[PDB]
Image (tube, rainbow, N blue to C red):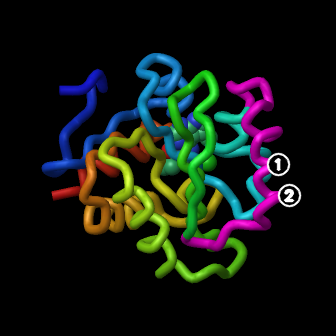
Amino acid sequence: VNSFSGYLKLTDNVYIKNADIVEEAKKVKPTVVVNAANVYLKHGGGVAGALNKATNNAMQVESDDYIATNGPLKVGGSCVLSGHNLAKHCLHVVGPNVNKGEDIQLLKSAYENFNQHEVLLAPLLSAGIFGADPIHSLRVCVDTVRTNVYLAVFDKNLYDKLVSSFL
Ligand SMILES: Cc1c[nH]c2ncnc(NCC3(O)CCCCC3)c12
Ligand SMILES: [Cl-]
C-alpha cells in the first residue's frame, strides 16, 4: 500500500492520472520523482522547468555542480540527485528529443532506468516539449518498466485519449 490517490490502473504495475507532477510531488513526497531531463540538466521548461521552479532553483544549482564534475548525461541515461522539497530523490532521465533527430528507439533505454527503483512518480518521457507522441511513450513505458510507476499526465484531452486507446 502506498499514498498515491485517484490513479486509474492500466496494468499490474502502471497507474495514470491527469495531474501536474509538481502537485503530485508536493502532496505525496514520493521516494522518487522522475524529471524529463536533457543531457545538460538545463531545467528551463517543460517538466524540468516546472520541477526546478518548485525547488526555488535549488535543483538547477545542484545540477550545475553535477555537470561540472561529471559532464553531460547520455540520451537514454539518467542520474539520481536530490528530490529537494518534492521527493526524497529525483531521477533525471533523458528521453530522446525527436525535434533534435534523436533515435526514438532510445526511449526504451530511457524507461529502463525506472527499473532500478521500486516505485516512481513520473511523466511520459519524450512527450510534451520533447516532441514524441504520448500514446507511443505510454506503450513503451508499459512494455519496459516492471517496477511500480505512477504517471502524471498534464493535459486532460491527451490523458482521456491515453486512457481510451489503451486496451
Ligand atoms: C509541463 C509540465 C508541468 N507539470 C507537468 N506534469 C506532468 N507532465 C508535464 N508535461 C509532460 C506531459 O504530461 C504533457 C501531456 C502529455 C504527456 C507528457 C508537466
Ligand atoms: Cl512538457
Residue that appears at 77% across and 41% down: 62
Tell whether 73 sits left or right of 58.
left
Question: x%, y% of residue 105?
Answer: 47, 81
Q: Residues within 10 Å of mark 1 (few under 14, many from 20)?
A: few
Could you tell me if the residues under marks 2 and 1 are in contact, i.e. CB atoms within 8 Å?
yes
Question: Viewed as shown, does residue 145 lie left or right of 72?
Answer: left
Residue at image location 77% in from the left, 24% down from the top: 56
Label 2 secondary element: helix
Residue holding disc 1? 65
* Residue 15 placement (x, y as % from top left): 26, 42
The magenta-colored residue range is 53-76
State the residue position of label 2: 68
Q: Residue furthest top?
A: 27
Query: Residue placed farthest to the front in the image?
Result: 69
Please tell me which residue is depicted at 51% across the width and 31% down the height of the picture.
88
Asked whether, in this view, residue 54 is left or right of residue 113, the answer is right
Residue in the image at 64% along x and 69% along y: 97
Question: Any magenta on residue 38?
Answer: no
